[PDB]
Image (tube, rainbow, N blue to C red; front, side, top):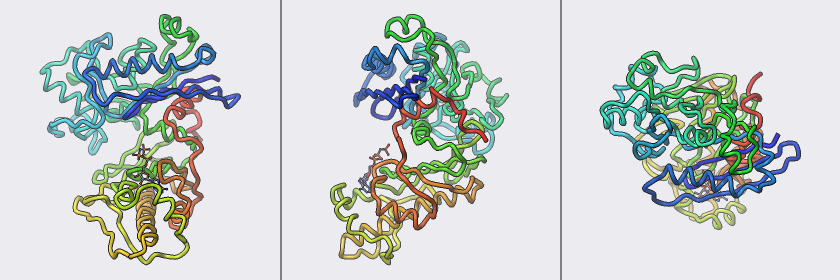
Amino acid sequence: VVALGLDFGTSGARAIACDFDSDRSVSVSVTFPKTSQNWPQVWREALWQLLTQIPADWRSRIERIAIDGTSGTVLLCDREGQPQTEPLLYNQACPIDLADLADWVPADHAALSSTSSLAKLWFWQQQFGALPPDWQILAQADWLSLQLHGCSQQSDYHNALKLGYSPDRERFSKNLLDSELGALLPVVHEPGVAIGPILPAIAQEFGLSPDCQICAGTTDSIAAFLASGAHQPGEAVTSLGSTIVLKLLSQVAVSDRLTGVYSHKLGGYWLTGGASNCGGATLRQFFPDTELESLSCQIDPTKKSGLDYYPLPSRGERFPIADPDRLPQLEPRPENPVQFLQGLLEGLTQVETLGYQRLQDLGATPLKRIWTAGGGAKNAVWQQLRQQAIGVPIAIAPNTEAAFGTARLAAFGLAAFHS
Ligand SMILES: Nc1ncnc2c1ncn2[C@@H]1O[C@H](COP(=O)(O)OP(=O)(O)NP(=O)(O)O)[C@@H](O)[C@H]1O
């Protein structure tokens, strides 16, 4: 099958069209502006740009399309999907009383945060006073796929989670549904399932098959996990970027209030994980990348540095163990920078080790292996430290592009995530 994955991320958008029987693909990109007074227009026009940059040869063969977008980026729209106010982005928080939400979701639900879609919907309820029942709240992914299939009030259970959806019982609460916010809530499908065929006009315009299907979308983080291809419980993806982000495939849902850990449903499985404040930014505080390569190649990982660092960039850890007063420990400082770097790397290694072990201690399926992404993935000394301390096979993820994970989502859905 020839499938299209569309990735709308934090700084840009990428389209990856894949023929999965000949292992062939084309990838195009668009970079977002630094500022805009009409972000919906930016996104939509980026969509048309991406479609346009895909060769006519491919567009005619594409049978399924899916879209991932940033989590917590929502739009308030009329019944035709026309934005009625500025979007609230993923990074923006809302000044409200999370106790106003407790009667709508279970205790410690992931939607109980000032940056969640539900908090933003409530914020809009307060700001507008009363929201017209024919209106709708749509995640970025939702709104963009709506541009293709014309079916309003449609979302997926990845995006809908922080809007107050409960993927364990697969529903919004009756309280929330019967509230004044209920009428703006979307119908929630599984990521990957066909919502409807592409619009006739859109198909004509862009030389797409009028029989092409638009699927339910997902978030860019989950899409990144999908890029790896991991589908057995116990498999994980570690992102060694500016911050270390762990994602672990589990047979069981796990969560933790104080560390903010939660789980998304993923087929018959669950994707859990957590994000540390430690990461590559700490490394950046002492070495540029070139120095990281040159010095890391001088490290022998089979000899302990003697150093026991907690490589926070600044004060306060969020995961594996919450502690808003945790200070960076980088003492004592050896005079050899090779040894200092080794100490830092051992520290970050301990962060990943503790993180995964903690996820398991909360009930998650025991770790089977690690696929690695992000800036530190290529560092084989760091990788060695990690395999020593964790004790599972570790490799570089076969693919890490969110658009590719989304193309896989379009082509195969979540079928692989079942026993
Ligand atoms: N050889 C290396 N070994 C270890 N860390 C490295 C190396 N090269 C770069 N880094 C770190 O990689 C970090 C950048 O990670 P990168 O993933 O590319 O960016 P990002 O901001 O995290 N965006 P994302 O890819 O979504 O996580 C920087 O802080 C670098 O210090």
